[PDB]
Picture 1: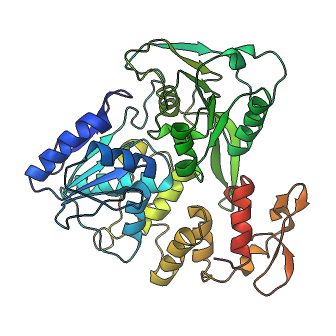
Picture 2: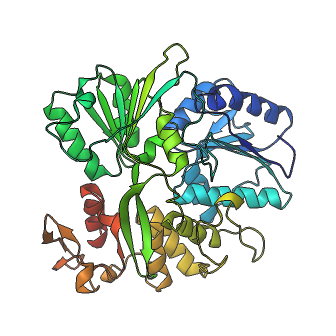
Picture 3: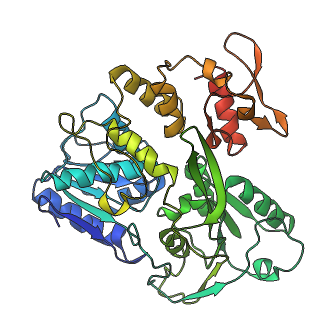
Amino acid sequence: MLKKKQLTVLDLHPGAGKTRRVLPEIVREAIKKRLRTVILAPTRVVAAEMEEALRGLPVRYMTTAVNVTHSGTEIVDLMCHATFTSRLLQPIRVPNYNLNIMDEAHFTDPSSIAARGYISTRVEMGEAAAIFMTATPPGTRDAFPDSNSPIMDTEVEVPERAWSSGFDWVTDHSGKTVWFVPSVRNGNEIAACLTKAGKRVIQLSRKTFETEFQKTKNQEWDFVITTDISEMGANFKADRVIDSRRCLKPVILDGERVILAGPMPVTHASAAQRRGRIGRNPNKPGDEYMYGGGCAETDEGHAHWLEARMLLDNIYLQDGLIASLYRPEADKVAAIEGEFKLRTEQRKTFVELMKRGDLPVWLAYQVASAGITYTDRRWCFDGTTNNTIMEDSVPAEVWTKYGEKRVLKPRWMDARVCSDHAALKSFKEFAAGKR
């Protein structure tokens, strides 16, 4: 695995020990061979788990999720996928790692796709080795991979709204269920219905995941209601997964706006990862997977792969060359390598709109490429009437940095800025000049 120009897909089934058994073997070998190594975790939660698996080995944890005093002599760095890509984009020196290990390498957030593209291009160049650890590489067509113990798979209608009857199997169960929903809002309704029926529910989503995931360890619970983020190595002591088999797909319409389409079917890889939360204990056969729809290749045309190209166009590789997407995921987008390359000052704007602004990649790009500076929020208010953002059926309003109350009507509409209450609160703060 460790030789230059190799990319290995470590595709052992979910729970086979890739993270806790195989990764520390790889790391010890890498250290013996004096390979400057990076290890990429999808989340802070996974980063902390890796610390436990790697404990005693000389690894520099480039994350505040781990409280360790470094020796200063580590040649192995560990950070999150997003942090890697972020550091590549910034005017900070990222070492040219000889060995690049991505855990949970199926993650489809734009920064993860971009990190795979950059890594795989370095490997293709003859410069580096890589290991992508995942049970479900791109284009997998098997939603029902092997597991540590047998799983009971049942196709069944799964509620996506509050229910009063007709789903007794949901609440009749006496164990612990992980339930995958397509969005925060849909999870909120299911969670409220379950709470009313006397169940203890924890909700997980990207913005809440570190904090809330701890509750699964510190409190007793009957259901975890989660979005797709729990496909990225989140482990639960559960005996059932309920899977709506649905997700939202960000779609760029006419090059001009982003909508959140669907819900629509998950990919096979997603379904396999959802299912793969259970069946993990070889002493507990008969964990249940209840699934409420089929799979489809909903990553085709999905905005994250175009956003990944926007990131990769703005990462230096060598002269004017630009990193390609990892080959098996490179047709998910119709894009021209280099089309989104920005000049130095617009690039800096683009970066800051993502990092400090917390704006979606696509929307950051629209603003930066328009020649707008990071603090100029006039665009949040000068869009067409149909870009009016609504809050409880009334136009959303903020006080501008000038002190004027205005309706939020962004020049470019990206549905991710108001996908839930939290998102809209954050965007309102942005529009107001508060970050």
